[PDB]
Length: 34
Length: 49
Image (cartoon, rainbow over all chains, first blue to last red; front, side, top):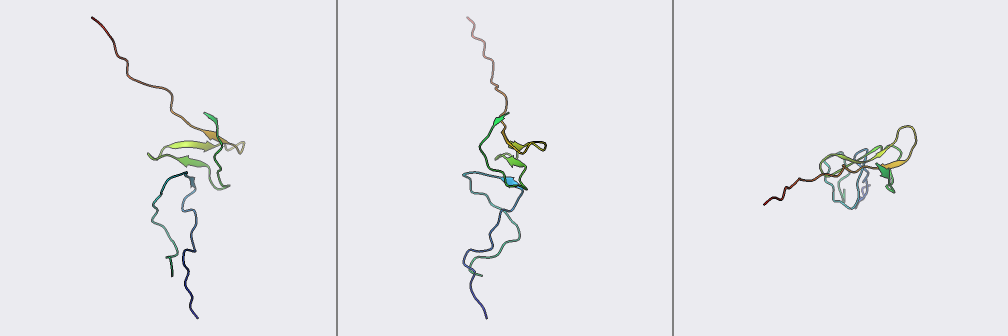
């Protein structure tokens, strides 16, 4: 069967730390509601 | 340098800045997080009559 992954499959893309920023990353991700 | 309260995950060793500059580091020998801050600078104005 099938089901919908709402906002799952989300990880930290890089080996670096950030804080209180909105960071854009083009990486291997799981699309939302997939 | 200075002690920092940032949390670096075990794989995380360097924290980058907006300008892709490391603004916080993890020491390879001791696993503690250090603050980074560029040294003071500024123009030198000369006031003269």
